[PDB]
Amino acid sequence: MANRMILNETAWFGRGAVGALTDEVKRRGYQKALIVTDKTLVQCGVVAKVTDKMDAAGLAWAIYDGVVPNPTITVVKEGLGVFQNSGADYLIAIGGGSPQDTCKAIGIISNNPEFADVRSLEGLSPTNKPSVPILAIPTTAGTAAEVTIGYVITDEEKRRKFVCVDPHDIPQVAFIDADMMDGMPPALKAATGVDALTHAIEGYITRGAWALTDALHIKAIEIIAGALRGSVAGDKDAGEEMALGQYVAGMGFSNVGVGLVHGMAHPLGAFYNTPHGVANAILLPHVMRYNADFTGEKYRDIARVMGVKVEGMGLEEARNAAVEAVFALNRDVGIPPHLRDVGVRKEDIPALAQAALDDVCTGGNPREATLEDIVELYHTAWTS
Amino acid sequence: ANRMILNETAWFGRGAVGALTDEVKRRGYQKALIVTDKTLVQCGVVAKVTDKMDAAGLAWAIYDGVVPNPTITVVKEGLGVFQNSGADYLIAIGGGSPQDTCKAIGIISNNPEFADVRSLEGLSPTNKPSVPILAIPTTAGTAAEVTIGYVITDEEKRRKFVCVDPHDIPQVAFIDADMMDGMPPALKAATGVDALTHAIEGYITRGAWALTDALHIKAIEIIAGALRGSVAGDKDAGEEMALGQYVAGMGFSNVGVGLVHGMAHPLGAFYNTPHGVANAILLPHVMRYNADFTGEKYRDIARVMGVKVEGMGLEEARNAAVEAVFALNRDVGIPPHLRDVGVRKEDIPALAQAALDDVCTGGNPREATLEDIVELYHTAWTS
Ligand SMILES: Nc1ncnc2c1ncn2[C@@H]1O[C@H](COP(=O)(O)OP(=O)(O)OC[C@H]2O[C@@H](O)[C@H](O)[C@@H]2O)[C@@H](O)[C@H]1O
Ligand SMILES: Nc1ncnc2c1ncn2[C@@H]1O[C@H](COP(=O)(O)OP(=O)(O)OC[C@H]2O[C@@H](O)[C@H](O)[C@@H]2O)[C@@H](O)[C@H]1O
Ligand SMILES: COc1ccc(CC(N)=O)cc1OC
Ligand SMILES: COc1ccc(CC(N)=O)cc1OC
Ligand SMILES: [Fe+3]
Ligand SMILES: [Fe+3]
């Protein structure tokens, strides 16, 4: 009956926020960092924005940049290997979900060595010790990996993404700095932006929802719906709004759950390596329609903060307005409307529906999802 | 760039103290010193926690010497008990007074150079985190469980001083209306308007930004909605108040308050006035004073406080916001004038000077002069 909230003890918000990291490291007396990132962020000079400030304050660092989209067991093991031979006593996550989730796995397994197979971390990880201290710097807007107690690792052998949930993995400090995010191509702003929206909407209507998370989620929907078109077009101010809104969504959904969008999205990541945000975006409006009659008054709120005039609308009419508002936003930021558009195969749907039913996220969905329900949703989402 | 310090872990709702035994075992702590006051031992509130700790086999000693507006003496005495207790962590059970006493003890224990206590004033230059604190509020009230601030009374200099330190943040908060139900109506009323003050002052403070604005406006809405119900003794309203007071804490701790708290602290020092009653009497008068320096923010306050602001000009809505606060104060049975609770006309000059010097006053959106604070005390005083 009582509800738990895990949050960052310390976080810095706004352009220039990464400038606070050298001070926070010195006040905690940490000796050497392993920075967990990917190739693109080294090559575009984003990592250098941090390693330059660390050089100027005389703080030692090694780099692991082997992280691929939808990080694998292989990538976790390889990164853990580098951390142990680096002599580091803390971690700095620089990137979107992929590096930040890779970083959490490494930080957990280092101080809980019985999980070295990594796949045994799935579900409520029964870890005894806190993670290696993590300092988190997101470069997408965003997975909110910096504030959530969750991370998603791809099992190549079993061809599935598995969710690990553990209060021990919470970063010590987050640095939410739109300066780190500006380099996102439009399509990445669009995808990660609707991933943030999905978190906010799924979180708002999830079974575990209560007053505090409702307050956070509805605020994040308002910020994201307001700013995402601006940000994809390349507006400085909208990009900062998105940086905050994606985080506020994290503060909610981490603590209560999401639903069938994330459940149906994870198999698409496993099977095709589909960007998490694109899969969520295509699925979100179809799953909202499916969930509609099981969400009380909450679609009125979604539609209103998304710019629709809901006064004088009936409950069912407002529920349609909320779904149409999400279709419209997807059209406007250039996310295709059908799963076949991103190479999902008609024949896989049975195996996809089964993976979706078994995914941790699906138990939070407000309408109780059957195998045949998920099959029909994939089909409706696949073509017209 | 703006910083947010929050609880890493907190539990919300009736029964939330049921999670403590689990949280202590997962952190491997051996023995607690519970910091509380006599009333909370006598009303069986402390026993609700020590019973659950007995059943899980977790050791505890108790310090119950905390008085309202905790003193340097009380901090020193409590620190003495903690060192001779063999405890390795702290459990705060009470409102601001025990929770603030507990933070001082936890800080000074691991930063022994502050044993005089009064050297903690301002941004405490502490090197080491506090002794781990687990916080259980029994008032709907100070948000001591989530803020990086604590207020200690200096008897010798006759002033309350604010200590601000990220090292004092509790590890876990337990926000449990079950622990709060035993508040007499007048205590629910006072601590409830202290929460409102935090929310309103925090909303309009100089350091305010989007995230704290979002928290504060939600807390104003919850408190304005629930406080009448809670004081009358409604179970559900008491839980709403328990959440709303906390959400206010998540904001103001990180950005600041203003001239209400600045003017309230001297009234605590001079007369031992309950913090919530002083804030309540002052709040509407300081809002009127601040009105012309708060942009559009009083529209928002008035709207979430149940006023229809759509047809209203800016100045008309600013008045509606102030009248909404007067009405709520009247309704929960708070005396409406400072003279009613024994504030003396002759002290106002010394009161105004203490207010000008208080840390809280630098956050106020309108820059306050000595003469301004003098005039505010006078207008707040009249029978
Ligand atoms: N600022 C940036 N500028 C340009 N490219 C960037 C930037 N930040 C990241 N990228 C690139 O975007 C691509 C996607 O990066 P991810 O980290 O995979 O993206 P994100 O959506 O943040 O994370 C998805 C991952 O997180 C999990 O929640 C989810 O299930 C999935 O595993 C990569 O090529 C990465 O290098
Ligand atoms: N649940 C309760 N049931 C009964 N009595 C209670 C309860 N909670 C508190 N009390 C009693 O109410 C009185 C006031 O307690 P405080 O802790 O002083 O109340 P609060 O308003 O929470 O604390 C204010 C303090 O915090 C600082 O911010 C402020 O400067 C001031 O020192 C005391 O006698 C205390 O025992
Ligand atoms: C169960 O809640 C979660 C579901 C999915 C994720 C990964 C993500 N960012 O989408 C994290 C979670 O938090 C515990
Ligand atoms: C300067 O900020 C503060 C002003 C007042 C207090 C005490 C209170 N809660 O009434 C705490 C503060 O810091 C968190
Ligand atoms: Fe996601
Ligand atoms: Fe206060």
Image (tube, coloured by chain):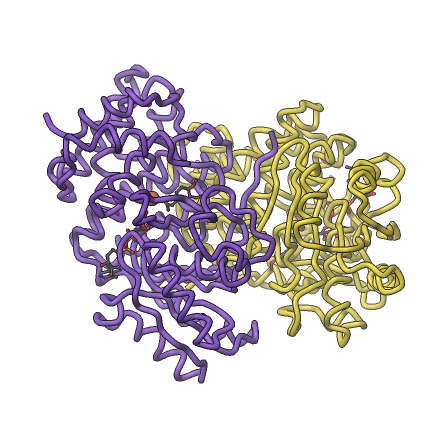
Chain colours: A purple, B yellow
Q: Residue A259 vs residue B356: left or right?
A: left
Residue B120: quadrant of the picture: bottom right
* Relative image position of residue B32 (x, y in whole percent): 79, 53
Q: Residue B322 vs residue B344: left or right?
A: left
The residue lying at 51 percent from left, 50 percent from top is: A7
Task: Determine whether B196 is above or below B263 in the image.
Answer: above
From the image, which quarter does the C terminus of chain A lie in?
A: top left
* Relative image position of residue A134 (x, y in whole percent): 47, 63
Please name whichever residue, A164 or A222, is drawn nearer the observer in this view of the structure. Answer: A164
| Total marks placed | 0
The residue lying at 56 percent from left, 51 percent from top is: A127
* Relative image position of residue A218 (x, y in whole percent): 39, 36
Task: Determine whether B306 is above or below A239 in the image.
Answer: above
Please name whichever residue, B293 or A324, is drawn nearer the observer in this view of the structure. Answer: A324
Residue A329: quadrant of the picture: top left
Q: Residue A133 vs residue A305: left or right?
A: right
Q: Residue B354 vs residue B308: left or right?
A: right
Task: Determine whether A2 is above or below A102 in the image.
Answer: above
The residue lying at 46 percent from left, 71 percent from top is: A84
Q: Inspect this view and state whether residue A313 appears.
A: yes
Q: Inspect this view and state whether residue A226 appears.
A: no
From the image, which quarter does the N terminus of chain A lie in?
A: top right
Task: Determine whether B115 is above or below B21 in the image.
Answer: below
The residue lying at 44 percent from left, 54 percent from top is: A117
Please name whichever residue, B279 or B96, is drawn nearer the observer in this view of the structure. Answer: B96
* Relative image position of residue B78 (x, y in whole percent): 85, 59
Q: Quadrant of ligand 1?
A: bottom left
